[PDB]
Image (cartoon, rainbow, N blue to C red):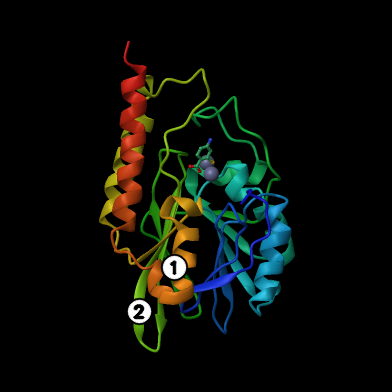
Amino acid sequence: RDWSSPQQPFTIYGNTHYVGTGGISAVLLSSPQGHILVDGTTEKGAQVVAANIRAMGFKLSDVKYILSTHSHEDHAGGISAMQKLTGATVLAGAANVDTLRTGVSPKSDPQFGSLSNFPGSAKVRAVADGELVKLGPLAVKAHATPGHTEGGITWTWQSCEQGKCKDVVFADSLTAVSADSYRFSDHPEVVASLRGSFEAVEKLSCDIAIAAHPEVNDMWTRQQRAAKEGNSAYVDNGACRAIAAAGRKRLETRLASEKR
Ligand SMILES: Nc1ccc(C(=O)O)c(S)c1
Ligand SMILES: [Zn+2]
Ligand SMILES: [Zn+2]
């Protein structure tokens, strides 16, 4: 389950398909009028994501938007390659646009000093908090969830099967992690951003959460459960509350560790 590893794709609910690697989520939201891809995985992973989309019966040229959670190599490293293969427009939070274009994270990032660069993408555009991305019948909402990065976005939509619908959340990372030289306690904007994000995420309408690191919401345990129980195994309307709680715990543990 490495970040670049092959992973046979699978449908989670309705027109929501997992097309990522063994270790990094990517989702295709499909329609007869064209598709939206969420995240690219790693640079090597782009070849996995591309093959996975085709394996689910879709054409790369029909992917019209690529949505970015955040601009680190594990989630975004494959975006540039996928953008070239698809012709899609890449959408991201305002403060991560430059990072996606250059593939270099800025000094505001708590991990700055310890991050690896990744390939810069063409056709990157900003979206605002609350903004709707529409493609034919698809409607995906952007939710600003900064803190791990300034431009982090958590993306939400509804998928349906014969009129039975579920709220799906592609949850950005909410993790307080840094270079050795960084003190969160010295950076009130980052702390406040993280805390606002925990609050936003624990309030989302959230039947099915797909975390950018899939194990954050136990994707592989759920998939194994789904073999007998069906796709209700992915459904858990407390999952966003739980992702937020774990984010809060990681930050509180970190701030305690920093006390003089
Ligand atoms: N070192 C870390 C930890 C956590 C994440 C994350 O996405 O939560 C990343 S990219 C890097
Ligand atoms: Zn990250
Ligand atoms: Zn990550």
Mark seen at residue 165: 2
Q: Earlier in the sequence, mark 2 or mark 1?
A: 2
Q: Tell me the quarter of the image containing the C terminus.
A: top left
Q: Amino acid at mark 1?
A: Arg
Q: Is residue 33 visible?
A: yes
* Residue drawn where x is 66% and y is 80% of the image: 57
From the viewer's perspective, is residue 117 above or below residue 181? below
* Residue drawn where x is 65% and y is 48% of the image: 77
Marks 2, 1: nearer the viewer = 1
Q: Residues within 10 Å of mark 2 (few under 14, many from 20)?
A: few
Q: How far is mark 2 from mark 1, CA to CA?
A: 21 Å
Residue 59 location in percent, x, y? 69, 76
Element type at mark 1: helix
Residue 3 shown left or right of residue 162 in the figure = right
Residue 90, located in which quarter of the rendered image?
bottom right
Mark seen at residue 52: none
Q: Is residue 212 visible?
A: no
Residue where numbered disc 1 is placed: 225
Q: Amino acid at mark 2?
A: Cys
Element type at mark 2: strand
